[PDB]
Length: 210
Length: 8
Ligand SMILES: O=C(Cc1ccccc1)Sc1cc(NCc2ccc(O)cc2)nc(Cl)n1
Image (cartoon, rainbow over the protein chains, first blue to last red):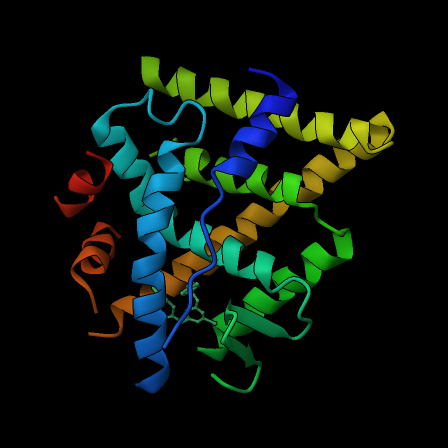
């Protein structure tokens, strides 16, 4: 596949923006739960995902589902500084919270804005999370890394086409990937927070994997 | 369990 077809394929597979309706938890469960149904269909449309086994697809989504949810919330909240756009009708401030995990989402949102992250780079970073979050947990592993190398080739291509020099392409690719380490830390603390809230049948299944 | 039916 191309570097251009990779972006358009990810751009076309983007999920929609859903709407919302002790009290705060209620809106977030229904939002996450309904938001994963589209994430399952989006995952199937990521190049190379359907090539994996049914068990591999399950495991990859079991450990990356909350990471993808958070990077998506950060993306649509990137242009609402100091706020988080859970939904078009659910734009919440830093005082409407939990807050520990709230501040981390805002810092990431303010960081993407600092780097002026583009949509073409967002869909790539989101696909990397889906394929990398569970790769370290034999012939199938080489294929996942083969796709990951292709997405990396796509990120660089987007940076090179943007006028960046080689030193700046490597620096931007490093800055983007280093944020995934913080996005994973946010999901780790978010899994402990939702496990300390004891929802939805599909959710609870995701809660028992961690 | 459930997750399998969604990808199925
Ligand atoms: O326990 C917490 C969160 C949680 C909610 C649902 C399932 C598992 C964990 S705290 C918390 C969760 C959260 N957003 C995550 C999120 C993003 C998009 C979306 O549509 C729904 C939720 N944000 C904050 Cl600031 N705080």
